[PDB]
Image (cartoon, grey):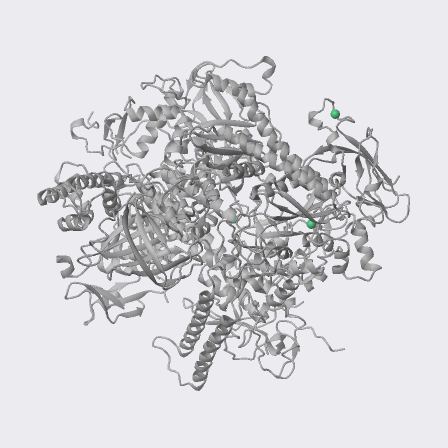
Amino acid sequence: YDRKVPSPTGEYVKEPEWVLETDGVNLSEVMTVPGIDPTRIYTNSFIDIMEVLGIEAGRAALYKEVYNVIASDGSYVNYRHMALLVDVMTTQGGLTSVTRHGFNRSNTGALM
Amino acid sequence: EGLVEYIDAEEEESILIAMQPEDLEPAEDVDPAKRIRVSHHATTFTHCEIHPSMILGVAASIIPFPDHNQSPRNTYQSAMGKQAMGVFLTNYNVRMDTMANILYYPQKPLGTTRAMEYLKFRELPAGQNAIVAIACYSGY
Amino acid sequence: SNTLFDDIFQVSEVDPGRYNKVCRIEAASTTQDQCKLTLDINVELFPVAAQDSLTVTIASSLNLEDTPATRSWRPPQAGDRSLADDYDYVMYGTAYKFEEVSKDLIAVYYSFGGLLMRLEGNYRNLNNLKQENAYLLIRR
Amino acid sequence: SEGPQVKIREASKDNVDFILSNVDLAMANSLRRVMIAEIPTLAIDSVEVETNTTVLADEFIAHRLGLIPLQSMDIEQLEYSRDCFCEDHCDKCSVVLTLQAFGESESTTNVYSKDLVIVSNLMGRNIGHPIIQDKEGNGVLICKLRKGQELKLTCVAKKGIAKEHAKWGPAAAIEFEYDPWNKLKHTDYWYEQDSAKEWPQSKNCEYEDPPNEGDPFDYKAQADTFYMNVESVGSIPVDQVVVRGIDTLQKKVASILLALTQMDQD
Amino acid sequence: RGNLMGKRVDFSARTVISGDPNLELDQVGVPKSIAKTLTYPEVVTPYNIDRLTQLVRNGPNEHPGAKYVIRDSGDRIDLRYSKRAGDIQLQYGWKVERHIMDNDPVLFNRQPSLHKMSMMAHRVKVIPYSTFRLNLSVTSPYNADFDGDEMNLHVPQSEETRAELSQLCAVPLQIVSPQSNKPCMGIVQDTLCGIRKLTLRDTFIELDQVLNMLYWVPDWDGVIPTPAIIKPKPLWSGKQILSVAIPNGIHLQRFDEGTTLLSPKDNGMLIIDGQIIFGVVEKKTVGSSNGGLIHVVTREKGPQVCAKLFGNIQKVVNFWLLHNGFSTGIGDTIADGPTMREITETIAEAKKKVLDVTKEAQANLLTAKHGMTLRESFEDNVVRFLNEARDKAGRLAEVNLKDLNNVKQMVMAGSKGSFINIAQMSACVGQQSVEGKRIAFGFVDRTLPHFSKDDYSPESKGFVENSYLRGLTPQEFFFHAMGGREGLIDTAVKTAETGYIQRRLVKALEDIMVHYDNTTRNSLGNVIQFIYGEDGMDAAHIEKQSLDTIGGSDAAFEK
Amino acid sequence: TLSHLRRTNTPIGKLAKPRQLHNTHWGLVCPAETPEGQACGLVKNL
Amino acid sequence: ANWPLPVNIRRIIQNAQQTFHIDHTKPSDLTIKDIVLGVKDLQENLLVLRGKNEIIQNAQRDAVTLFCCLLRSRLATRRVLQEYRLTKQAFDWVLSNIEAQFLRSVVHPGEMVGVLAAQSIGEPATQMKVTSGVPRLKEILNVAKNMKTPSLTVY
Amino acid sequence: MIVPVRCFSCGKVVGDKWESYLNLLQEDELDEGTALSRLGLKRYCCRRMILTHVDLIEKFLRYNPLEKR
Amino acid sequence: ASRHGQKGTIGITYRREDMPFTAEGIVPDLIINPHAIPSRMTVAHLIECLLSKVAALSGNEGDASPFTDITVEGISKLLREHGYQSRGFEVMYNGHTGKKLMAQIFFGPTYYQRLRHMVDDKIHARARGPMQVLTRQPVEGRSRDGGLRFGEMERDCMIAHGAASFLKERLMEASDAFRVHICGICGLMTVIAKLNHNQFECKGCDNKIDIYQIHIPYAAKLLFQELMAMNITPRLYTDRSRDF
Amino acid sequence: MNAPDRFELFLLGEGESKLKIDPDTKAPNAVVITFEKEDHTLGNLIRAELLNDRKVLFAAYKVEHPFFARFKLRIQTTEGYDPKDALKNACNSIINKLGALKTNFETEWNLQTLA
Amino acid sequence: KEKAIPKDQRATTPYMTKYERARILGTRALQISMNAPVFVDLEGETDPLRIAMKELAEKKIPLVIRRYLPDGSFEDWSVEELIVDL
Amino acid sequence: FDMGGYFIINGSEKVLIAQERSAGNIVQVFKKAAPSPISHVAEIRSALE
Ligand SMILES: [Mg+2]
Ligand SMILES: [Zn+2]
Ligand SMILES: [Zn+2]
Ligand SMILES: [Zn+2]
């Protein structure tokens, strides 16, 4: 992959780095393997991110997953629209689904 | 006489069919406008298609040059060809139907299809030959 | 009113580009070795060929006596006298940029309704060109 | 007299071909618009059906009858039904035609426009008679009948213009062309390799000299010397179509002048 | 869901919609019969006592007219059957239910109505015929065409809703969408193609035509601009006349690839004081794009000024295109002989490359790419070669197209089409894929009963070598039909699945609102965000800007 | 009328994708005649 | 460096230059003290929250952090005097417009952002190695324990 | 169902040429192209009016009359 | 619609003297936008027009069967033999002014079809009309003077616009609106109101001075009554019991 | 059905005038004339004739909507020249030119033999 | 009245919102349509909405907006003192 | 031109749409998903006409 890191002169230059892509997720055990950068490891499934790094880390991971889907087709959506959806999904100290088993099990009035 | 044979989908799995007798059957400059046709250089043909155009149905046999169209457009025409006013029957004056539509002056197409002969479209046409201009005239 | 710039140029080359009526001509002044002109000319009304000599003049107004959307343009009337009578090709446009090329070289950009002109010269010959509207007169 | 010039190339009872020179494009275009849409003509407008045992609908026959071209040489002597002081219609603003056909023969019998009979008082006029323009002497095939079928109806003809309905249109296609050599650069010829070889030359190209093949474009030239071919449907003579087209356009301009004068007083 | 959340309502109308380039952006054409059915209860006041009395006299069968008279006591008097006693004497405080007139604000909607711009308020314009009429520029927000689509109309019945509808839902207020902080309305179709043609350097307009074009702009100042060319013939450039529609004081600058101050290709854009200096006008300028002319105008001069811009540009551009013309035919999809010879060789070279790989795999001398099987690696190589063959073939055809080619003209202006459309119509349809893979062996080890088993050549697994101009062979026709069926199935399935997703999302966030303390809370009062969007701004007012401090080298920063 | 007299219907728990135009359909059912709605692919024409 | 931000400063600067017809050659009358203090006190008027307590004031300061960075970068002492050639009258005009434009961009209380956000995310969905498109969006919205193609990225 | 009275495009009368057209095809042994030109139909708008017309009236006339006099 | 998926409605009708005309005097019976061709790639539509033009000029029946040896170039050659542009382009004149159109128009015959959808069978409006017996809302169906559905999605868009008052007007004044009396003790709609005598009573609570009237949709009344028959007590109250 | 009666294209209605002349405030000595029950046939002809007059500075016409048969004509003349007088001269020129054409056509037609 | 914030410590935005303007114009327009006394000089106008717009421009609308907080507290803002900047 | 092929029931023309079904008396082997004790199943819908 190509990542833009600051150059010693002060400019941003693209340098190549070797990145490993995996099928299957074991975040807890892989994160401890020596030789990798634990401060940058990312997982496709935001569920394991929440269980290992916390709700706030899951919040960022959830937004990135949503952003990728929206940006996969080239469409652009304002950040706050996705941020609000992600914030609602993580406001109850956890990842609440948008089905009848998630937001519809709260206490917001029977009529709603 | 053994000149033609009925073949089902299961039996097609064990035969080799030729698109047309013109080129594939005979043992084997070229016009730049003709489509690129593959000979397939096969010398074991067991059957020959009556005509490739017969793979189409009743509704798809009315389209002129359907092979010069994007596939989804042909599908739309098939559905729309069934909603076109015409002459469903010649005895519309003695039948009491819930609803019936009859065109005043039906005309047969200027560009027709050979399969169209057996659908009686030249006897019961649904449409007219209008003079059409493709232009941006008034923005309407 | 009064001429802001006048000189005689020799057309180095003519480029029709992708257009059929407008050509971009590169010319250099015959008296100054640091003056060049890039101009777009409607060759349908004023054909231009290579190695041709053109007298280029820029004026702020067309009326003879000095008078230093201003006013609604009206068709010329019989007996009207103006600087345009002494030239063959006349254009009206606006200056939209003043660029410094070197210590003493100044380039002025003009746009006559989409036909762009670039006048490059020393600081002491293009000092009368202001960021305003001006007429361009060309005589063969 | 030293105004627009006219030169007739081919004259017939159905088509007139001429060159209209020393005229402006606006006038030439307006003339053809008036010839198509604003020349009064006589046509069947209402039909009363007494008996109809045919295989066609009553409105189907009525529509066909309205498209039958009728003589309109003396149309100016007729009056508009809207401008006449009559209950429904009279001999001063209308013509009545009757059609009666019965299937007396075993074979199919054809009903033509020659079977229409005028039952009104023409008062010495020259209008109403259906136009017969074929060798056999029959007219338009209005309907077909078999044995035992009868058609009985009455037609009323009124004067109108094509703007109200196309059936009062007295002129067929009108050819109109100018500058066959494209010397005014009014068209950008679409082509693949060479426009001249791909675009056939108009038949009018022989009446004008070709371009000098290298001369500068003439920006002072204005379109003139229009080539026109007016066709007539047969209701009125083709020459009368052009003559009355000019008359109609002249009257319309005069009406504007008259209206302007009336405003001047007030 | 069927009777409380959504229910059928009165005072509404439905009919087919049509396009009218002579209608303002916010105007809607209403059929006369519909206007005679829908009514608005207007209160009788000293200001309209005379006007309302005339409507009562006109009766309910003559537009403009009235249908009912409601007294202050609540009694309703039907105008029909009432004329026998003569016209009613009106009094202050009464209500006269009269036909909807011109300029009456109405709500115009089209289902499924997936976003707020699909339901906007328009101004009534009673018209002949039995169809609704609306401006072309507002079709994109509605996602509507004129192939038979129908739209719903709703008439407010109170002054409060009348003012609320016209001050929040008005079309001009929806020009800049908050979904992507970019305009959702722009010049489209004929006006987009015409404006691109009109702004070319070769477009010059004579005096007679210029006067007509100038007069077509309602807000024209009555001053004829000086022609770009004064002698030997007064000619106005296309940019000069179009600049009249652009309001004064608008500045816009854009540089495309290779664009300089002396634009050699006439690309880019430069507008000073509402005058176009150089550059062609296309979708990047007058379309629904970020930073375009519409975005600049609506943010600098307001929404009402921007609404007038839509009409002015359309009126001037449509008139010019009416007298200029623009068409397209078979001749626009035909490439010259040399291009076809190059295209045929290009495809043959790709086939030969595919032949070589198909021979190495048969010899087992091909090593599978890491992470993929031998067969999967072979398929990827074949697909890559064939996909590139179509792209290269299309490039040759597109380059050969002349500037006069109508299909090329449409693509350049952005009105319709794209590169792939030109390539498939003229050069090569390409490889047909089902389930993201080549045509599978429906039969035993073959695709159709015309090839021998284990045939992996492009012609066998669904490579359409011909173009739509040349025609598809029967094998290609069936393979192409198979690919299209995948698209039709996806369209049906995608619509159903996506509709459920949208409903779920809306219901989960329907009770979230921004409060007067700038915090985002739901119906329970729980705080979702302590400030909307983490910055407190509105998406409709956001624009993309460059941060000059983050970028650049240290030396550049110091300088 | 002719099309309606030659139509076929496929009642849709199954593990397959019957809506696709299978290769064996060549020459037996029209590859282009199918409804555009919920019945796409399931209703075929001979 | 290209990010969405409320006020388009570049357009405002251009309007000031074109409105007052900046000479671009004659020296300006601006002073270094005026520019630095003019920009500094402008940042104080960019009020999103109006509480008079420490917690709200800190939140207000944080809310305009990024915008102030853009404001300072564009209205730099060197850039204003050297690149823009702004006059004191022009500079004051720019400052007033920036304050007015920023206050117009603030979200209006009572706006139903929740429905707007849902429609802005759902409307694009109708037009839509790893799972993408609607199946992935369904995978995200529906919190499914087992996803089709889980993956890890290791640096 | 029956030959139109007028050409749709230009309004030329074509309803009085149907029998002549049929006669030319049958007795004169002329192809449809030559017969159309001999009838004076030059513009292709008129040619398609007679060339593509279907005479459904003949089929209807085969049914016995509903009401005989 | 044509035989190639191209369908559309009549935008406007023009008389003969307004339509563009060729040098021969032929005016189109129909005008379609060029923009429909590229995105849809219905090349057969263009070929058919070229073939149909040749067929009419030659008095023949065009052969448009899918898989034949007929090529576009062959049609073009025959068309050129007739004195027409090989690609079907013609020089046209503007009907308003008579001036030549700068561009040449693809012009020829094509077979078009009239579909069953006519606007007169769809146009309909409703100010007021019959209501359903059960829900007391506008009936369904054009033939029965029914109303139009203001569905939940439409409600969502109005909530986004912030037009709270308009939303109430659609749901109450433009649809079912019912006034009911509720008891101050029990929130049930079981108050017997003798409006002629100006008397109210809530049997079971034994009160006549604690009655309130509320405006709710008739459907809402039906829901609560249905719930009451289901042993559920939806109680409507006018005063708050808990602070926000 | 909402199809207007076809006679509304040319027939003048009740309480309606053929011409409606109103002064234009956008430019000096400019007037706008509204023609009722007229189309491009007269607007194009009148506008073209006006442009031939050296004392007319601006002359243009437009049809706001094709549904209605009315067009607007804007005329601006030099100071001291009445726009109404300019219209008078233009109409008279058209009438005179048309009359000359009619006579020329008739004399040429009388010289033919086939018809 | 502990739910009424005194004018000295109001912390809401001093700018009238689009929703506040929409209701104020609609409410005042409705009152005008029902024969309410007009407090602004009329230079010729019959539309109640237009008259309301004229009143708002001159700040002659005798109404106050009671902005509610998510806890039940509220602030009273007069139309005259609210700046109309949008 | 009428081709028949339909029934007249209560005055209404009714057409019997052909119904597509899987052939009987044919052995078909299918694979099941991982969450199942059975990996492969051979099923025959025995039918006697
Ligand atoms: Mg549609
Ligand atoms: Zn009479
Ligand atoms: Zn014709
Ligand atoms: Zn009680």
Q: E27 or C31, which lies in front?
A: C31
Q: Position of D170 compared to I138: left or right?
A: right
Q: Position of D112 compared to E28: left or right?
A: right
Q: J20 or B80, which lies in front?
A: J20
Q: Is residue E450 above or below residue G101?
A: below
Q: Position of K39 compared to D144: left or right?
A: left
Residue E418 visible to the viewer: yes
Image quarter in which the N terminus of chain A is found: bottom left
Residue furthest to the right in view is D105
Q: Is residue J52 above or below residue E411?
A: above
* Picture quadrant of residue E359: bottom left
Q: Residue at x 53, y 44 (%)?
A: B140
Image quarter in which the C terminus of chain A is found: top left
Residue A57 visible to the viewer: no
Q: D72 or I180, which lies in front?
A: D72
Q: Position of residue A52 (x, y in %)?
A: 23, 60
Q: Is residue D50 above or below residue E337?
A: above
Q: Position of residue I24 (x, y in %)?
A: 65, 52
Q: Position of residue E31 (x, y in %)?
A: 54, 34
Q: Position of residue B37 (x, y in %)?
A: 58, 75
